[PDB]
Structure formats: structure tokens, C-alpha cells
Amino acid sequence: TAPEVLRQWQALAEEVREHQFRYYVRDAPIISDAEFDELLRRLEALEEQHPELRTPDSPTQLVGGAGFATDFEPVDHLERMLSLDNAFTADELAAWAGRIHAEVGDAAHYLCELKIDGVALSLVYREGRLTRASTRGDGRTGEDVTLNARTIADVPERLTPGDDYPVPEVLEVRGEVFFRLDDFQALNASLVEEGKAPFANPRNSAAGSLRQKDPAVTARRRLRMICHGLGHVEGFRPATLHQAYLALRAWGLPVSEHTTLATDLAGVRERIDYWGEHRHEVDHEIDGVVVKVDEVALQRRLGSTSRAPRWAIAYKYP
Ligand SMILES: NC(=O)c1ccc[n+]([C@@H]2O[C@H](COP(=O)([O-])OP(=O)(O)OC[C@H]3O[C@@H](n4cnc5c(N)ncnc54)[C@H](O)[C@@H]3O)[C@@H](O)[C@H]2O)c1
Ligand SMILES: [Ca+2]
Ligand SMILES: [Mg+2]
Ligand SMILES: [Mg+2]
Image (cartoon, rainbow, N blue to C red):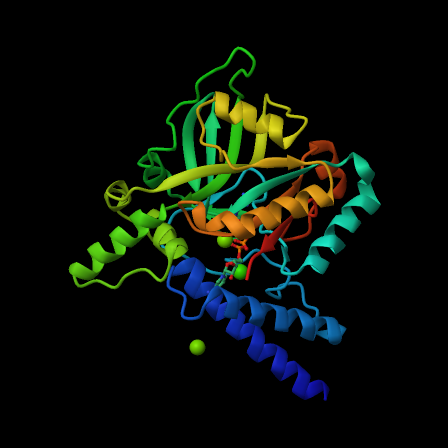
């Protein structure tokens, strides 16, 4: 029934939007990430089954966080800041790799990174000086948390020039802000002893600690950061992500030591199996592995959707 299917879509879309608000705006979700993911998959399946439900501002097409207002100063990113599509099974991973191979061939190599379950942050360095830091927001416009980001010890005020890597005129770099697991638990126990509510989990603790109107609150908390992507850059043309990370390292920016470069899907699957067994050994919350086409020229050819790059996928663990 066209009437009945539409009401079903409306209820599900409204529910998805409610939880996106609770997660992205309040850092206070009321259901688990797994439950949220199933709701979003249900919405997508409803749209695939009934094409008349495809609507441009559905949660299935937008960066989570779109459509909400907040108390922070809005600031436009220099380049779109996107989400990631997911693989929850081996079949979904292999379907992605096949699609890569069908478009760009065997030339693609695959960078395999730990997917940090933190809060996204975008930093802008102008002539080597940190001038702005922003949350993802709706992917185009973020929230100004520059003063909060300056308090993070991992985030430098100034880039250190290298002889091999001159400082770019403009560097927009993206990464994850997070707590180590012991610090996450210590903050929750500290909050509970003060009578306040603890955070649900490491992600919301990090996001809530970063998104503070008073940056002194952020300063008291041992936030960490790892850079894992590039936005707009001027005066720097890395040919590959792994070469970009060499420059970021040289400049004094934090990069993960756990990343590996695989030549093919078999190599990628070996690394995903490895972290399935060893992710409990990482001192911060990991919700998967991000697989990325390493060659920047191939990323540009693969492109991106309205909400995620086509050249990367997040494999998510159970
Ligand atoms: N529980 C709830 O009510 C609720 C509501 C909305 C969303 N969520 C959760 O939010 C997530 C989906 O939203 P999302 O758009 O933030 O997606 P995501 O976290 O699944 O993937 C995209 C994000 O991965 C991050 N990331 C971490 N490590 C990375 C790496 N090495 N390389 C690149 N990026 C890396 C980036 O910040 C990027 O924004 C899911 O985990 C979902 O369950 C939960
Ligand atoms: Ca979302
Ligand atoms: Mg409700
Ligand atoms: Mg996340």
C-alpha cells in the first residue's frame, strides 16, 4: 500500500534523525551503535524496495549531523568532510574490492588503518600555524572548536618544516579525537564520584569533552588525536596517502603507527583478520578497519558520493 509504505518510511526516517540528533548534537545516544546501524539499514532497504521513497535529504544520502543547529559558531570546511560506507561481512568487503578493481584495476594498493571510535576533527594550518579546528557538522559546515583543539597535547600549534617537506601554504587535515580506554574509565569514575552522569562509551566521552563551550573543560581532559585524511591543501601534492603520512609525521602531526599497506584484497583480508584477533590490545576503542585506495590519482578517479568516498570502506567488527 503506497499510503502504508510512506508512513512506514516517515516513522523510520524520523527515528533515524532523532538518534542522529542525540548522537551528533548531544553526544548522548539512547540506543547502541549496532541498533542504530540496523535502523539505518532498514531505512535503506525500504528505499531500495520502493524507489518512490528515494528523497534527496533522506538520512541514507546525507552526512550524519546534517540538518541540525547547534550552540557553537558555524564554520565552513575548505573541502567536504565525509562519512564512510560500511562493510559488515566478507561479501560486502569483496563487493567493494571488486568494484575498485573493476574501475582502476590491479594498480590500486590498499592502506589498512584502524578505525578509531572517536569524534571527527578538522584542522586548518595556514603557513604552518593552526588557525581553525572544527567538527564535521553536516559535512560542509562544522562547529568551531579551535580553542578546545589547541588544548590537545597531540595537536601542535605550528608545523615543523622539513627539508623534504616544506610547510604547505594551506593544510586542512582530518583526524580522530579520542581517549585512551583507561583515561575514558577514569573520567567516568571521576564524573560518577561528583554525582554527574558518566558518558555512554569512549566515543561520546571524547565528543562531549571536545564540544565544550568552555575550553578549560577540554584542557583538563587527556584527549588524544590521530590524523587520518586530507581536506584542502595548497602547496603540497602527495601522490599517495602513505607519502602524505610521511609529510604529516615530518610536520609533527600525530599519525597512527598501526597502519599497513596491502597490495591486494588478500593482503587486506589478512590485516582485517589480524585486528579481529588483536584489537583488544590497542589502548583505545576500535570499531573496525578502514581500507583506502592509496594512490591519490585513483581516489580522484573513483570519486565520492554525497556522503562518503568511493575509494574507502570501513570494515566493521561484530
Ligand atoms: N547510537 C546512536 O544512536 C547513533 C546515532 C548515529 C550514529 N551512530 C554511529 O555513528 C557512526 C556512523 O556515523 P559516521 O558518519 O560518524 O560514520 P563512521 O564513524 O562509521 O565512519 C566515518 C568516520 O570514521 C572516522 N574514522 C575513524 N578512524 C578513521 C580512519 N582511520 N580513517 C578515516 N576515518 C576514520 C572519521 O571521523 C569518519 O567521520 C556509526 O558507528 C553509528 O553506529 C550512533
Ligand atoms: Ca549517522
Ligand atoms: Mg523517541
Ligand atoms: Mg565513528
